[PDB]
Image (cartoon, rainbow over all chains, first blue to last red; front, side):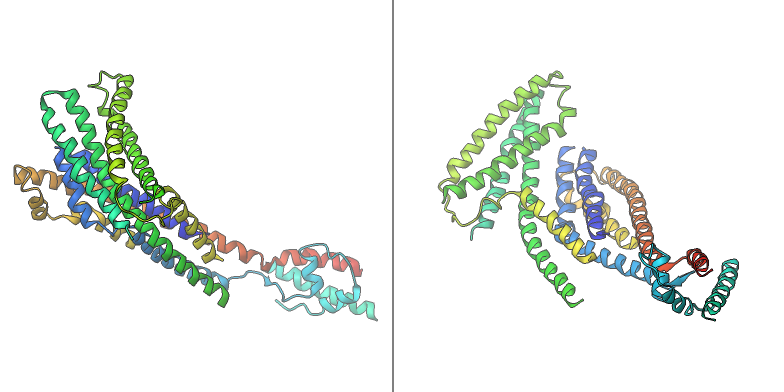
Length: 144
Length: 84
Length: 101
Length: 100
C-alpha cells in the first residue's frame, strides 16, 4: 500500500508545489514589478509554517490516519461475506485435494474425512447433497 | 554554535548588499533597455536568490528537525511492531 | 575558522547561486530574446559577463568570509540541501513500509 | 478526507489570506487607486476560484482512486480463505470414482 507516501507526494507536489509556484505565477500575472514583489511578501509571510515540511508531514499523517481508519472499516464490513464454505472447516484430505494434488492417498483417511462433511446456488447445493449421500452409501457398502 | 549566524549573515548580505546593487542599477537604466535588462535580470536573480536562500535555509533547519522528529516517530512504529 | 568550514559554506553559497543564475535565465528566457536580438550567443555572453561579475562578488564574499570566526565541527557531508532531501525521501519510505507491515 | 484538503486549499488561497482593506493598506504606500486595487482584488477573487475548482477536482479523484485500489486489494485476500463449493464437488466426483 504505502499510502502515506502517496498522500505525502500528493500534498508536496500536486498541492504544495502547485500553490507555492502559484505564488510566483500570481506574481508573473500581476506583472507592475513591485506589485508581485510585494505579493510574495504579506500573503507568503501569513503562509509561513502552514506549508512547512513539518506541517505537510503532520497533515499528511492525519490524512493517512483518516484513510487507514476508513479502509479498516471497509475491510471489516467485508470480513463476513462468504458465499462458500471456509477453509479449516473440512478434513485434511479435502483441503489438500481441492487446491492441489495430495502427493499421497489413503482410503481410510478419505472415508473418515468424508464422513465429517456438513449439511448445507441451489443446483450446487443439490448436487452436493446427492453426491455426499451417494459417497456415504459407497463407504458403507465397502465396510459391509 | 554558529548556524543562525551563518544563515542570518547570508540572508543579511543579500538584502543589504545584493538586492540594492541590482535594484539601483535597474532603476537607473530607464534610458537603456539593454542595460536596464541586465539589471532587471540581475534584480530577478537577486530577488530569487533572496527568497530561495531564505526558504532553503528554512529548509535545512526544517529538514534537520523533521528528520529527527520522523526518526522518533519511527521508534514509536517499531515499538508497535514489537507489541504485536 | 576552519578551511573545511569556510569551503563548505563556499560550496553552499557558490553552488546555490549558480543554480539561481541558470534557473532564472531559463525561466525568464521568453522575455530575454526580443531585446538581445534573439541571439542565444549573446545570452551566453551575457551569462559570462554576469558570471564573472557574480564571481567577483562571490570571491568578495570568500575573502571576507575567510576571516569570519566559525568552528570546525560541522560536517561538510551534511551541508548540502539535496543530500538531506534524499534522506527525507528515504526515511519517508521507511515510515510507510513499517506502518503497513 | 476530501473536506480536509478542501479546507486546506481554501485556507491557502491568497484572497483568503488578505482582505480588501488589508490588501489595500500593504499596497497603499505603493499603488495609485483603491478601485484599481479593487480590479486586482476582484481579479484576485475572480481568479482565486478557478484554481480552487481545479483543486477540488484533483483531490476528489485522488481520494476515490486510492479507495478503489485499497478495496480490490482487501477483497483479493478473502478469495484465498474460501473454497469454491464447485471445486469441492469437482474433488468429490473423483473421490466417488476412487471408491467405486
